[PDB]
């Protein structure tokens, strides 16, 4: 019975940033539009395709 | 260009599936047909190169060499018939396939649009040549000769590979057309100097340059007759072709960097011809004469004047034919006497008259008797060098003198004098040998009629 998790109705405001964390960095640009064939294929030296 | 490449490839399955009695016949037939087809490429445009496709192109420089290779293959087969007549069918087919692979590689080299593709194929030519020399050689020095040839060529080529990849990274393309239209001058920085050296040294090794020509005597002497034919007719011209192509992006640094190589070649022609004068081996003499004649082309390429390039192309074609013919004649004499000592066989003119006439005509072409294409090229190079510096005429004329001297010396020692008494196995010349000599001489004399075809793109 003393081991049961209990509810507490406190008046103290819930800490907005308890860890005092710094601003997280902006994510890298995610994906893009559709895939299209390579402009000239494998442009590896003499290969044309 | 596939109109030439594809039949050349189709030669291989034919040779592998041809009957043991028909291998040589089929190979010769279809090789001659392929040469006939390649003749169409000679119709070069006045300004634009024949850009068949993105990968293959031809100009008035590439087309004569292509025709030369396609024409050289059948003659090589004819020459190889004699000594490779006791060989088992599989090995004979193997030899024919090596020759066909070499021809295919050379065609692709001369038609490749991309510089790195040219490098790949021009270094691929080593494998068939090495196999031919080391496997079907008659002496014990064949292994060392093959090692020398392979290592010289590779030591030249690998820095060229690095330089070509560097150019691809910087310029963005190695296509000859783009490389020529987007040409940018090179500065005098040490980096540019070493890039120029890397781009030039490989081709300098390919066409024997005095100091780096040690591989040629060994290779030509030890290699079988067909191998020597290609080695002295096309494989050396590979260096000239590559150098003429690559000099487009090596200016104006060429003006400053040519002096070492220019002096080396201008003295080397004299030195090698003098060496020819005092040679005891016939094939070695022919090889050293080749060294001198190629040093002339090296000078012509380094000078970079239009007349020099025209003369260089003409000389390359002429020397290819002449050197191949000389090696064939020496091969016939060697087969009869089983020795390469020049003084061993004497007075052959009495025993074999027609072969002596072939010898005479070949030697006349070697000494550049007017109006042979040999003389046309030599004279053009001489005039270009005279424009470069008047002092050049001294060395050029002396080299002409020494060439005439050693060529006539070869003719006199072999095809003149009292016949050797103990040598009794000199049979009458075979029809095949005479036909080989004729197929070497007649095209050259006909080419003299219309030199414009073999005068290069700067005509």
Image: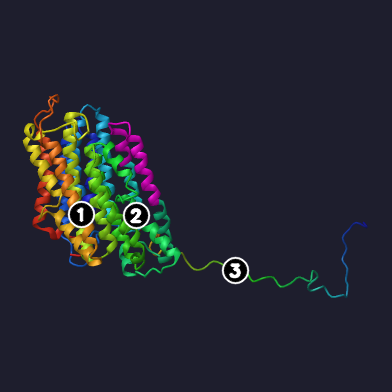
> Which comes sooner in the sequence, label 1 or label 2?
2
Labelled disc at residue B134: none
* Residue designated by label 1: B398
Give how far across and how far down residue B28 sits, in percent.
16, 40
- As measured in the structure, the alpha-carbon distance from the residue carrying label 1 to the one carrying label 3 is 75 Å
Task: Look at the numbered disc 2 and give the secondary structure of its residue.
Answer: helix
Task: Look at the numbered disc 1 and give the secondary structure of its residue.
Answer: helix
* Residue designated by label 2: B117
In the image, is B124 to the left or to the right of B356?
A: right
Instruction: Please tell me how crowded label 2 is: few (under 14), some (14-19), or many (20+) other residues with Cα within 10 Å.
Output: many
Give how far across and how far down residue B247 sits, in percent.
32, 62
Quarter holding the N terminus of chain B is: bottom left
In the image, is A44 to the left or to the right of B412?
A: right
In the image, is B418 to the left or to the right of A34?
A: left
Residue B146 visible? The answer is: yes
Q: Residue at x 20, y 34 (%)?
A: B18
Q: Please state the chain letter of the residue tagged with numbered disc 2 in the rendered image.
A: B
Q: Please state the chain letter of the residue tagged with numbered disc 3 in the rendered image.
A: A
Instruction: Please tell me how crowded label 3 is: few (under 14), some (14-19), or many (20+) other residues with Cα within 10 Å.
Output: few
Q: Quadrant of residue B420?
A: top left
Q: How many marks?
A: 3
Instruction: Please tell me how crowded label 1 is: few (under 14), some (14-19), or many (20+) other residues with Cα within 10 Å.
Output: some
Q: Is residue B75 above or below residue B184?
A: above
Magenta span: chief secondary structure: helix
Q: Are marks 1 and 2 in contact (CB under 8 Å)?
A: no
* Residue designated by label 3: A28
Q: Which residues fall within the magenta stretch?
A: B129-157
Q: Quadrant of residue B10?
A: top left
Q: Please state the chain letter of the residue tagged with numbered disc 1 in the rendered image.
A: B
């Amino acid at each position: 019975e003393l081991s049961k998790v209990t509810k507490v109705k406190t008046d103290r405001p819930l800490p907005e940033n308890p860890y005092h964390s710094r601003a997280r960095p902006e994510p890298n640009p995610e994906a893009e539009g559709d895939l299209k064939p390579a402009k000239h294929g494998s442009r590896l030296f003499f290969w044309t395709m | 260009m596939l109109k030439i490449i594809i039949p050349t490839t189709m030669l291989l399955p034919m040779t592998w599936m041809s009957k043991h009695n028909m291998i040589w016949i089929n190979a010769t037939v279809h090789s001659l047909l392929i040469s006939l087809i390649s003749l169409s490429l000679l119709n070069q445009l006045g300004e634009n190169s024949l850009n068949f496709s993105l990968t293959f192109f031809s100009d008035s420089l590439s087309a004569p060499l292509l025709v030369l290779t396609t024409w050289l293959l059948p003659l090589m087969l004819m020459a190889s018939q004699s000594h490779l007549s006791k060989e088992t069918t599989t090995r004979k087919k193997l030899y024919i396939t090596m020759l066909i692979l070499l021809q295919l590689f050379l065609i692709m080299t001369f038609t490749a649009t991309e510089l790195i593709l040219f490098y790949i194929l021009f270094e691929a030519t080593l494998v068939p040549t090495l196999i031919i020399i080391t496997r079907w050689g008659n002496q014990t020095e064949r292994l060392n000769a093959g090692l020398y040839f392979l290592f010289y060529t590779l030591a030249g080529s690998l820095p060229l590979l690095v330089a070509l990849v560097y150019i691809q990274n910087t310029t963005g393309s190695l296509n000859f057309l783009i490389i020529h239209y987007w040409s940018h001058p090179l500065s005098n920085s040490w980096s540019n100097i070493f890039m120029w050296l890397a781009c030039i040294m490989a081709f300098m090794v390919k066409m024997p340059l005095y100091g780096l020509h040690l591989w040629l005597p060994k290779a030509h002497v030890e290699a079988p007759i067909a191998g020597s034919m290609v080695l002295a007719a096309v494989l050396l011209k590979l260096g000239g072709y590559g150098m003429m192509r690559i000099t487009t992006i090596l200016n104006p640094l060429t003006n400053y960097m040519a002096y070492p190589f220019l002096m080396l070649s201008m003295w080397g022609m004299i030195m090698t011809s003098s060496i020819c004068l005092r040679q005891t081996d016939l094939k070695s003499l022919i090889a050293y004469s080749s060294v001198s004649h190629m040093a002339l082309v090296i000078v012509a390429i380094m000078i970079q004047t239009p007349w020099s390039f025209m003369g260089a192309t003409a000389l390359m074609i002429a020397h290819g034919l002449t050197s191949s013919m000389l090696f064939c004649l020496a091969n016939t004499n060697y087969e009869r006497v089983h020795s390469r000592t020049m003084i061993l066989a004497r007075g052959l003119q009495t025993l074999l008259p027609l072969m002596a006439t072939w010898w005479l005509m070949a030697s006349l072409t070697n000494l550049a008797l007017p109006p042979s294409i040999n003389l046309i090229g030599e004279l053009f190079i001489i005039t270009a060098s005279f424009s470069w510096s008047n002092i050049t005429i001294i060395l050029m004329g002396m080299n002409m003198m020494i060439t005439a001297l050693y060529s006539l010396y070869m003719l006199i020692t072999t095809q003149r004098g009292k016949y050797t008494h103990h040598i009794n196995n000199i049979k009458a010349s075979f029809t095949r040998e005479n036909a080989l000599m004729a197929l070497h001489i007649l095209p050259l004399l006909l080419l003299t009629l219309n030199p414009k075809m073999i005068l290069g793109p700067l005509y």
